[PDB]
Length: 171
Ligand SMILES: CC(=O)Nc1cccc(NC(N)=O)c1
Image (cartoon, rainbow, N blue to C red):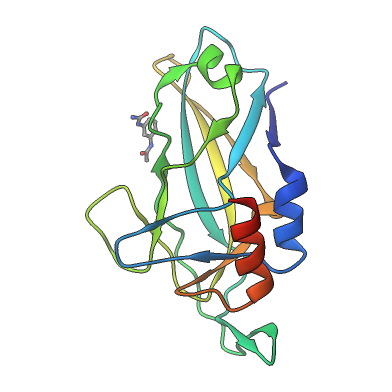
């Protein structure tokens, strides 16, 4: 059985219990913490591409009011985010299972942009999600996995200084 697990859940949970925030810029900003995933149960000899996308966790705009994150009242449908291909893709199962799969080079933006960067809507709450796509074989296969522990609100600057302080302490 294909097993997908979050590396450093300990750290992610400190961020989550404060409400995590991720900066988005016109040019694209890398994530901290970085999503790193432990994968076992692949065919070491099969081929796999690793994809990352961001699910809108709810349909609302959030705002930091009197030191607390609060949803707007006016939901709008959230079109799914674009997919980021792990730059090591494609590679053999053995490659993916030899060390944590680390999405250190994904950049989050607030503007439709050339390539690489993933455009998110500022002040929306997102749940990272990967897809493991078996490629080259005759039978194409997709396994998806969500990471609740890694939820964040996309922000153009940090609102909760407790987050600013954790980001610096652990970077
Ligand atoms: C929509 C999309 O990009 N999907 C996808 C699927 C398998 C492989 C790749 N590319 C690759 N370089 O591994 C991309």
